[PDB]
Length: 252
Length: 260
Image 1 (cartoon, each protein chain N blue to C red):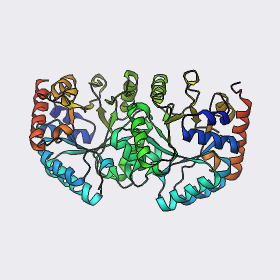
Image 2: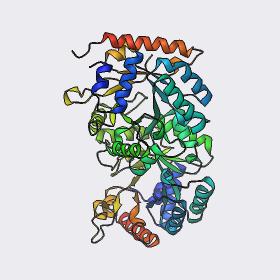
Image 3: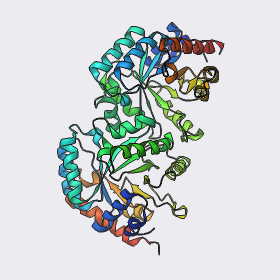
Image 4: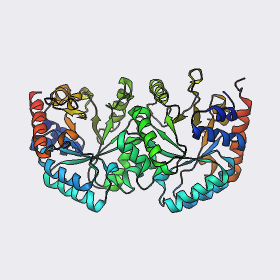
């Protein structure tokens, strides 16, 4: 693969290019997944991890005190201050106005602040076209979508055929679909696609996933639970991910 | 398959038993899918369709004025008055506390009023066990779950293997998973399962109606194994009389069932 700096210069999606540049400049491919109960805990952790991450994965559906003024506003300020993007957990899985409104409206109004979101490909390309239209109608700011190509939960049905079907859906819009949540490389380079591979469940080891083609490591509890110091863990994982990245062979 | 009445008498799920009995007693296997923008129109249509349906599929996410007091309260009164269950559209697709709270809380608090909900199987059995525990914690009222085994949207990935996987997941809990949203019989009888097959995208092949002719007919799906026909805009859009359409679809649905 090309370096993050190089991919930032050629990628067709503005959000992807912005992400690749952040990764290059901050020497980090670390995404912090913070699934906490209160806005207070969330803001505290984001403050500590901000300098070490390229992306923050939020989980607004489990927050007990979510609000545009108390949560999104300070979150947007942090994103700006420390330079990292926002990725909301909500796994969209519908089409038409229903999915458009689940992404754009309601109390959460996700499309108004989340740079990146993800969707299940099972419902077909309609989820891609629907979310794309909703994003355009809500903001002029860059928005991108990841397809949930490979799940990690017990008994998941994201088989080889399902993943293949998901990759095919992704090919329908290289401008909006920037990549996948997956455990391995999804190819695509020979066809003119440059997909971001974000991999959760990392603690598999960093060296392992990065060596297999992961562009971003998604780490959750391993960064802040069990009395851990998030600042320290943020640096430990960033270093491990960056060094793993420097080691893998680039496209020459 | 045995008759709806017979299936109600031996079903392990109290929600499915209640639904099969409603179907027999009202002579209907019709589910009205109402995806309107306002509660006012919703309540008006439910009032007109009430006597003709066994199930109402709501779409709370598209409502522009949803409220527990103004929407759910009268909706429950209507289901009690006309005797039909509530099925909310929301296609759950996550696990753990995330899926539990998406189902139990928020502004919608779906588990508090929706007798039946549906979930995507792609995430695995965790979605079943999670929604099940949430239901038990939220209300004493029986709750049921449908797995989205066969989707009808363009380019869906509900292949033969995906569908089989979903059916295997449903087998993990015959008490809570009452059936599927599908386009054909999912079997299971020889294994001791009696799944409700609910099928959307149904029409009546009306003269000169190209749009409606794009859908499979009531006769086609019921003959194939569908237990409940899910009908949408065909019941109320383009100036149609909901009460008239409800009777037309109920009638065709039941006659096909008896023929079966």
